[PDB]
């Protein structure tokens, strides 16, 4: 397989990916980074949506 | 911002046209650390 | 004239711009990071 | 004996226009110079309630808004007061209070600011006559007076402390952003285009 084919297969399985702890942690980190970016831009509307999404994704055990 | 201006000037006669070329430095934007692979894809590190 | 990239600054671990400042206790284990690690150092090469 | 340098005797017949004074000092031509603090302001204009209410400004920055509110409420003002007999009188909101110890205090409303006086010699007040380019003396500035808040519990001091304490708390200049692609991609693609047009230009010049 080529590198591009590997990336395509990984994206396909990510679309198929229901949940994975490593991927959930990565998604939460990316969401936190996006939230701080929105905070620095004084966007009070996006930050509410990002906070709601973070609350929904979180609550681990 | 300690040195916020780079200035070049030129009195063109080649009609006296004094042209000043100046560039200013603005905000600083930082990001979270990121890894850029050889293939081209970038991801959080 | 827009956000031109001037370089990459190493990030001190557990500082405000580190990815481990968030992530709580549970996710710190999934990332293979020791919760007893205190940060305060850089990772070069 | 340092002999006088000027002996020509040349004289100017300049006549200066002088206006009558609304008041005249008694017993001594003495005045006190007072430095104006940041929390105290002077509004020489007569107080106009409607423009003042219509021109109140609201800002997001809490520190600036609080400072403006404090300086506005502490500003020395005056207005025309209609007397009960139908006449008009000048009415002010500021007074000077002298205590039993002899110290002086500037009062605006319920706020009291103490005065600290330091004697100054060879300090005078003059009136400028720009059209003739000469300076006419007015009186002597014997004492320099500083205005100080009376106590910690004074509302002006507490507001100043709050404003200055929260002013230095806000400090964040760098703005975060999210990188979606390689930061070096622009440089390499533009270098490729520049090399391409270099090759084309070299070919054109060799063909020109």
Image (cartoon, coloured by chain):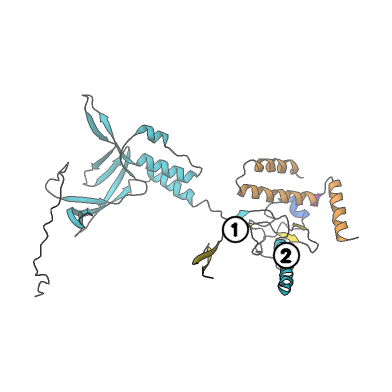
**Where residue D120 sits in the image (x, y, percent)?**
21, 58
Instruction: Please state the total of marks drawn on the protein image.
Output: 2
- Of all residues, the one furthest to the right in this rendering is A1
- Above or below residue C8? Residue A20 is above
Which hue is chain A drawn in?
Answer: orange
Residue at (74%, 73%) from the top-left corner?
D207
Relative to D16, D43 lies left or right: right
Magenta stretch: give its range. Answer: A17-22
Residue at mark 2: chain: D
Q: Would residue D153 be visible to someone looking at this image?
A: no
Which hue is chain D drawn in?
Answer: cyan
Would you say residue D196 sits in the magenta stretch? Answer: no
- Of all residues, the one furthest to the front in this rendering is D208
Which hue is chain B drawn in?
Answer: yellow
Q: Which mark is residue B28?
A: 1
Residue at (13%, 56%) from the top-left corner?
D14
Which hue is chain C drawn in?
Answer: blue
Mark 1 is surrounded, within 10 Å at the Cα level, by few (under 14), some (14 to 19) or many (20 or more) other residues, namely few
Residue at (78%, 54%) from the top-left corner?
C30
Identify the main secondary structure in magenta: loop
- Kindly report the distance in space between the C-alpha atoms of the residues bearing marks 2 and 1: 28 Å
Provide the residue designation for mark 2.
D193
């Amino acid at each position: 397989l080529s590198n591009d084919e590997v990336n395509s297969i990984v994206k396909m399985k990510q679309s198929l990916s229901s949940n994975t702890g490593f991927n959930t942690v990565l998604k939460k980190a990316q969401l936190q980074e996006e939230l701080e970016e929105a905070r620095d831009a004084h966007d009070h509307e996006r930050v509410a949506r990002i906070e709601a999404e973070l609350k929904s994704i979180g609550a681990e055990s | 911002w300690e040195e916020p201006r780079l200035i070049l000037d030129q009195p063109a006669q080649h009609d006296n046209i004094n042209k000043r070329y100046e560039i200013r430095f603005g905000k600083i934007y930082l990001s979270r650390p990121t890894m850029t692979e050889a293939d081209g894809t970038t991801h959080a590190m | 004239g827009n956000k031109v990239h001037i370089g990459k600054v190493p990030i001190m671990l557990r500082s405000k711009f580190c990815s481990l400042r968030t992530l709580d206790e549970v996710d710190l284990y999934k990332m293979k990071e020791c919760p007893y690690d205190m940060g305060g150092y850089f990772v070069i090469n | 004996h340092t002999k006088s340098v000027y002996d020509n005797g040349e004289t100017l017949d300049i006549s200066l226009p002088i206006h009558p004074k609304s008041h005249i000092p008694q017993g001594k031509q003495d005045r006190w110079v007072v430095k104006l603090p940041d929390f105290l302001d002077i509004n020489a204009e007569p107080f106009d309630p409607r423009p003042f209410e219509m021109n109140v400004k609201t800002h997001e920055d809490k520190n600036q808004e609080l400072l403006d509110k404090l300086i506005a409420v502490n500003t020395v003002r005056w207005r025309y007061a209609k007397s009960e007999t139908g006449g008009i009188f000048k009415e002010t909101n500021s007074q000077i209070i002298q205590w039993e110890d002899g110290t002086y205090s500037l009062r605006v409303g319920s706020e009291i600011f103490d005065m600290f006086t330091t004697n100054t010699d060879d300090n005078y007040l003059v009136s400028e006559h720009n059209e003739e380019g000469i300076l006419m003396t007015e009186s002597t500035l014997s004492k320099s007076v500083k205005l100080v808040p009376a106590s910690f519990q004074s509302t002006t001091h507490q507001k100043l402390a709050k404003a200055l304490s929260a002013k230095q708390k806000k400090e964040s200049y760098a703005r975060s952003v999210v990188t979606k692609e390689d930061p070096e991609e622009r440089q390499r693609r533009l270098e490729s285009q520049e090399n391409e047009r270099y090759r084309l230009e070299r070919r054109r010049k060799q063909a020109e």
